[PDB]
Image 1 (cartoon, each protein chain N blue to C red):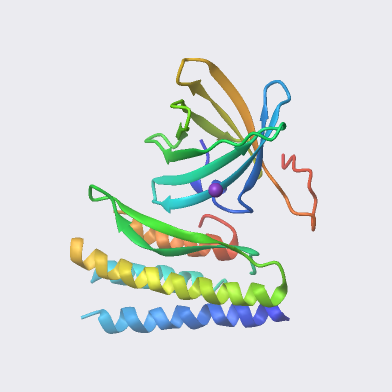
Image 2 (cartoon, rainbow over the protein chains, first blue to last red):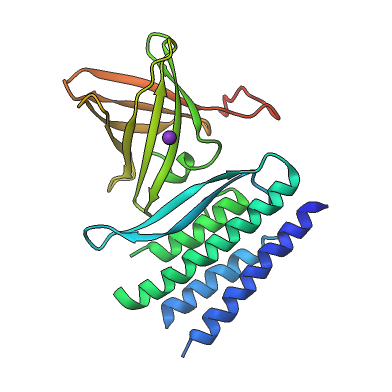
Length: 127
Length: 121
Ligand SMILES: [K+]
């Protein structure tokens, strides 16, 4: 069904980040990130009507990272469901990029938070 | 004491049932998110039509309990704990700034497509 195109669209960005992280390895934290993402890939083959979209990351007055939220993209209809999946994965890759760069600069549970939040927004459980 | 994520998901609409029957609708929006903490702006609506405004700081403590601090435009503060009762309902228990205590059942609004009633027990 239409669900399938979404599942495929998931594994797409998944392998995108497989590529980026593997080329950047030249790094054990990078490998644990890679582990967790391929760990979640095997559950792909769900559609949530309400999707949280982050604009980016802002560091507070101290060494506390924050994920700034744009809005929740409530897709009324089906084509909007696909199109919110699109905007969502695009902003998610965006924040992921800023996140890797920040973690190598500043050198915290932020990354596993990011990963498990993807797991949550897709499969529906904390794990 | 309940996993933090239980508060982000779903539609950002709820209803606060007070101890006496007063129902006040909550239209809220999460601005910032951390592994430990959460920030959100909240807009209440009384049954007569009065609105309010708040900024609420949610966080999980050391022992895993959910605690919150709410800031209002009346110079009034609120502080308390949030215990999840089911997937759509969590019970706030706490103390206002002048000292008066309270208990509030914050339920979330479920869409028409499905089972509205949610015991989930
Ligand atoms: K609002």
